[PDB]
């Protein structure tokens, strides 16, 4: 099935996460906020991959990321 | 029980979805983004209805909608 | 485990909820909207506390709050 990622990432590191998610085939949506918030539905078995991306891009290096992995009952694509 | 809809819809079609959701008694919230993102808690047995609305308003006609249906453990109304 | 709160609160009462959540050790994120929308992952056994806060701050006194409590499969903190 599928999952929903809500990754709260720092704004300075938002630019590069946004670019690098694209390069890893991750379709994501940025909710503007000032500390930017991302939304990304990924496959059940691609959770470890996206978490790696978010960590390599942002976190305590300075930095800091907090992400939630949430269940999805249904996915539709019109 | 209840569900949560996260419908990522195109901005040109956001205006009309926003209006038409009201006409179908769907209380929804628009998170501004440029590709706008909607949030809408609907009843367990009104998922098919709202999906119809979103499709009739937006999708590949040009267009394109992507929606997630997510479980809700509790709903409160103060 | 943990939960995710999506609290749709009125804008006039958003300022004070935002301040008072901090005073109760609730790390939350505000998604700008005009009727503002909040996001807050809290512990499994701190749902009653945050609901109290939201009610004391906003609701029908004038007012009005609507909140969803949603399951979280995984929480990560980089």
Image: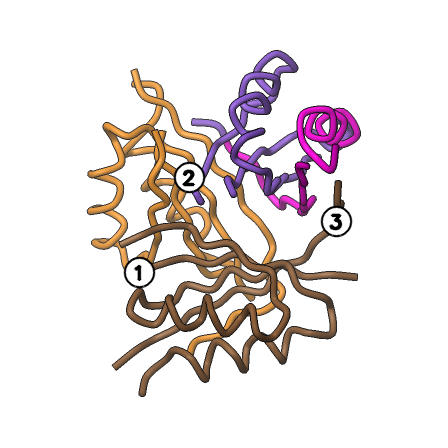
Chain colours: A brown, B purple, C orange
Residue A13 falls in which quadrant of the image?
A: bottom left
- Residue drawn at 48 percent across, 31 percent down: B29
Quick check: B2 above or below C41? Answer: above
Secondary element at image label 2:
loop
- Decide which of tag 1 and tag 3 comes sooner along the chain: 1
- Residue drawn at 36 percent across, 40 percent down: C52
Boundaries of the magenta span: B47-76
- Residue drawn at 52 percent across, 43 percent down: B35
Front tag of 2 and 1: 2
In the visual, does B15 lie left or right of B52? left
Give the residue at mark 2: B32
Structural distance between the alpha carbons of marks 2 and 1: 16 Å
Secondary element at image label 3:
strand
Give the residue at mark 3: A75
| Mark sitting on residue B50 | none
In the visual, does A24 lie left or right of A45? left
Give the residue at mark 1: A35
């Amino acid at each position: 099935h599928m999952k929903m990622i809500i990754a709260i990432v720092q704004d300075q590191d938002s630019q590069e996460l946004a670019d690098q998610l694209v390069k890893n085939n991750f379709r994501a949506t940025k909710l503007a906020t000032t500390n930017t918030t991302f939304l990304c539905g990924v496959n059940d078995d691609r959770v470890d991959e996206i978490l790696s991306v978010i960590n390599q891009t942002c976190g305590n290096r300075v930095g800091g990321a907090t992400v939630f992995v949430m269940p999805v009952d249904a996915f539709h694509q019109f």
